[PDB]
Length: 103
Image (tube, rainbow, N blue to C red; front, side, top):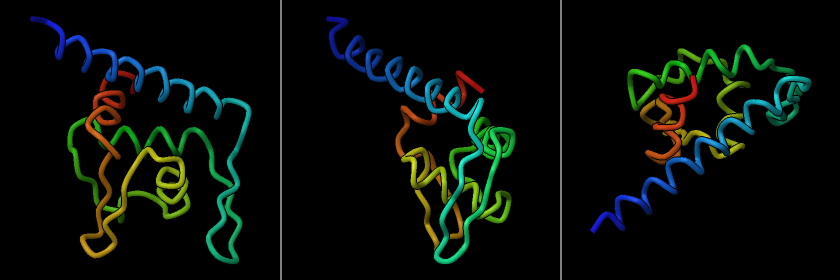
């Protein structure tokens, strides 16, 4: 049966719509990111640049991305942070696939 395949396809497409909505919300908004006492404005462009890094690699070094940018992307459940490793990964393979399909 195609059933499990189709269920996964549901999950995959859904996450694509979700990521598209996330990214479209940035068109007229520059998020203000809170990091303790810091308040830092970031831009859609910066966010796209960081996510594009995940197009060819599942696991990305935090040193490639401004902290304000990846903190936002973690807060927003796009990425997970491994502080000890100094790396980030998509929060699921659905998120990864969506990045690769959309960016």
